[PDB]
Length: 111
Length: 111
Image (cartoon, rainbow over all chains, first blue to last red):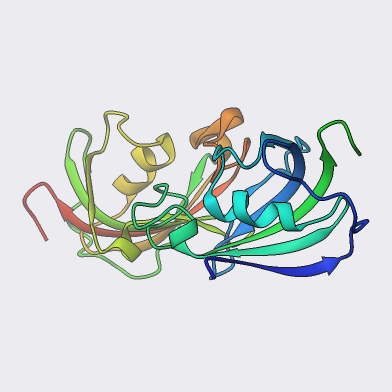
């Protein structure tokens, strides 16, 4: 598909994020070539966002809710579920695949 | 000091960019961790700009002019002559040294 999760470390396996849930994550995204383009880990500023509401790239919206609380996975997002052909210039060229390490630290009030 | 050059390949050793010149070049930028953050070279869209007048980061304003027409060098630019404390979000963290591969394709009307 447009997004695929490799599971790297298992979450709790019951608590998954449904739509409109307020997700809290740490991540690091690279390009296929290996360049780190953004990392909430490096900034020690854990990213919070609402989920099924399209405030983040489709690959994220669609891919995160399949992680349970505490899970550590990797998201592979095709340009089509990413920043499209346009991209996010200097950082993310157009038609860029994305590889995010992702850690789910909380769903709404949960941690 | 602030920017350091490393001539990789010699230009014509006659034609140097003086201030207020319009330069044409082909560049690749990387963080100290090997991550490429921008590259006219990959876009195949050679960047053009005026040099002494602060329409690029200072590291360039002061490096590019040390190069002659045709030269390939490597600029090393401290955060201080770069993006400084703020950096450039997503791609370029705060307080980041930069390493630009640079090719001086043209000075005003020369190639």
